[PDB]
Amino acid sequence: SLLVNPEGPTLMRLNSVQSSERPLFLVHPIEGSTTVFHSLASRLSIPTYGLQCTRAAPLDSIHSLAAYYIDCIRQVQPEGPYRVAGYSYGACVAFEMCSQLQAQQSPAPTHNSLFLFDGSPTYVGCEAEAETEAICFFVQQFTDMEHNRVLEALLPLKGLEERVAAAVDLIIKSHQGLDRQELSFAARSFYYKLRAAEQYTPKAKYHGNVMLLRAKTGGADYNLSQVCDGKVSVHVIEGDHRTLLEGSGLESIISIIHSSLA
């Protein structure tokens, strides 16, 4: 899976457009990288930035992460409204960022544009078990090892740091050239990211318009109507969860969002 530079800037420039036009801000999927947005960003005639998940990111909750990302983007664009989007895990974060923006200017309606790429605030035994499960899933991507084997290696360890260290060692054994500090940060942050997303529930009903770009190859609105009482527009995009932001699906996405990004 993708890795991020733990010391990388939170707010990354994704294309070379330099103007005063309101930028599009794109929130990372769970891997925390913004490289998945390269194609989309290259198509746009507005400055496009990504929020990547680095050592800077507060992972205690989706609320904290979203608050931090809002604070970052408001440095590039001091005045709203904001064009914010999120992909997969990032959809939950992007939704929370807009939820916080709504609360800050309440009862004045927001005119923030929110695009959810195949994700939603809903579509994202004990703590030692939770760490183990999360770290096991993380290892299973990078390695070919059977679930039970990774489980018996991680489950009895002392705590999160020991699980992370053993996970990095397991991954390195299979892929010697991978960077140990990037893997250590990715593994530890993966647990915190899952824990935050699983505890997340929006604090209030979202009144703003939401656009969901759902992958054609798999509720129809990813439960958006349950947390949104504004206009929810759902578009079915060619491709799967990982390919809708490329090729034909990205062409469709560009045509659908063009008028909003004017």
Image (cartoon, helix red, strand yellow):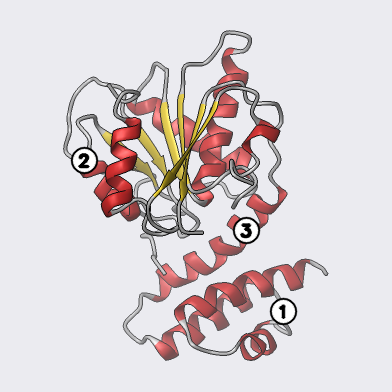
Q: CA distance from mark 3 to mark 2?
A: 31 Å
Q: Residue at x 59, y 18 (%)?
A: 104
Horizontal side of residue 34 vs 195, given as left or right:
left
Q: CA distance from mark 2 to mark 1?
A: 48 Å
- From the image, tell me which residue sits under label 2: 43
**Residue 231 location in percent, x, y?**
56, 23
Q: How many marks?
A: 3
N-terminal-most mark, 2 or 1: 2
Quarter of the image where one finds residue 174: bottom left
The amino acid marked with disc number 2 is: Arg
- Any part of residue 13 in sight: no
Q: Residues within 10 Å of mark 3 (few under 14, many from 20)?
A: many
Tell me the quadrant of the picture where the C terminus can be found: top left
Q: Seen from this angle, which residue lies furthest right?
A: 125
Q: Which mark is residue 158?
A: 1
Horizontal side of residue 128 vs 32, given as left or right:
right
Horizontal side of residue 55 vs 129, given as left or right:
left
Tell me the quadrant of the picture where the N terminus can be found: bottom left
Q: Residue at x 72, y 79 (%)?
A: 158
- From the image, tell me which residue sits under label 3: 194
